[PDB]
Image (spheres, coloured by chain):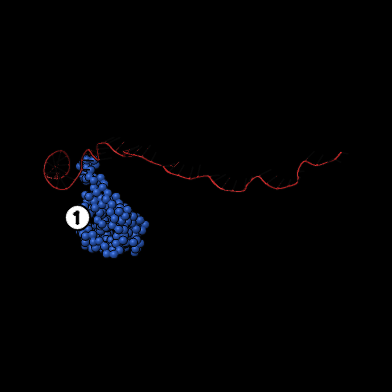
Amino acid sequence: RFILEISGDLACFTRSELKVERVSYPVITPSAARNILMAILWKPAIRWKVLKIEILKPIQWTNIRRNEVGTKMSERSGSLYIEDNRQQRASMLLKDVAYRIHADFDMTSEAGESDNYVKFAEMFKRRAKKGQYFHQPYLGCREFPCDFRLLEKAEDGLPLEDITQDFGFMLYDMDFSKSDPRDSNNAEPMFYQCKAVNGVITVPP
DNA sequence: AGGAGGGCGAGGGCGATGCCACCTACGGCAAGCTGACCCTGAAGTTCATCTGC
């Protein structure tokens, strides 16, 4: 288990419902929490698994309308001209977040030869303490960086001390099981937070 | 010639240096306008275009 300690000035774990008008999930999504732990280290042998988020700064919001673009980019049309494809996505962002994601991982079917769980474990451990990553972890949106740390047990004060808000059914981790290589056909599994007692435990599927 | 050229101690004492009121009146402190254009939508289909046949 790794008690990595994602933190950042802003964060947007955009609720699936309020995607066009981004309203962040009140805490780190276990998908966004996990994909962060793939940004620091991943390989198609490691399969990350968030075991317990722990909120470390209170759920505080700042709305940010960004002139986002409306349409994907495409081989077909060789430019956007944003002023033609403009959209103004509001973003109820999570200001001053922090999350100590108690996450571990497993070995996939394609673990390869060097399937050593300890190898990837210490690889990620060195990456996180050193600060290395494949990708500066995205707090839900890459516009938001995860000023992370690989805590050992506990090195920050979690604010939802007494029993606190149950954020309801949050996106857990989009189901890339039916997908071929590179996540084509997925689905969304979702979870009762369970509550936020003081740091939400997640459910392994 | 050799003189002596003041010695003394007073040089204010007393009180008053203001009294009276007034220190503003009047009214106005805004008028008139604008405070935004423009777009950017969901949802769906069409339509032009592409790939494959």
Q: Is residue A42 left or right of residue B51?
A: right
Q: Quadrant of residue A112?
A: bottom left
The quadrant the C terminus of chain A occupies is bottom left
Q: As rendered, which of B41 and B27 lies closer to the eye?
A: B27
Q: Secondary structure at mark 1?
A: loop
Q: Is residue A54 above or below residue B47?
A: below
The quadrant the N terminus of chain A occupies is bottom left
Q: Please, what is the three-letter code of the amino acid marked with disc 1? A: Asn
Q: Quadrant of residue A107?
A: bottom left
Q: Quadrant of residue B3?
A: top right
| Chain on which label 1 sits | A
Q: Colour of chain B?
A: red
Q: Residue at x 34, y 64 (%)?
A: A153
Residue under pointer 1: A186
- Binning the other alpha carbons within 10 Å of mark 1 as few (below 14), some (14 to 19) or many (20 upward) gives few
Task: From the rendered image, report the letter of the chain displayed in blue.
Answer: A
Q: Residue at x 27, y 49 (%)?
A: A64
Place of residue A138 in the rendered image (x, y in percent of width and height, measured from the top left): 29, 53
Q: As rendered, which of A112 and A136 lies closer to the eye?
A: A136
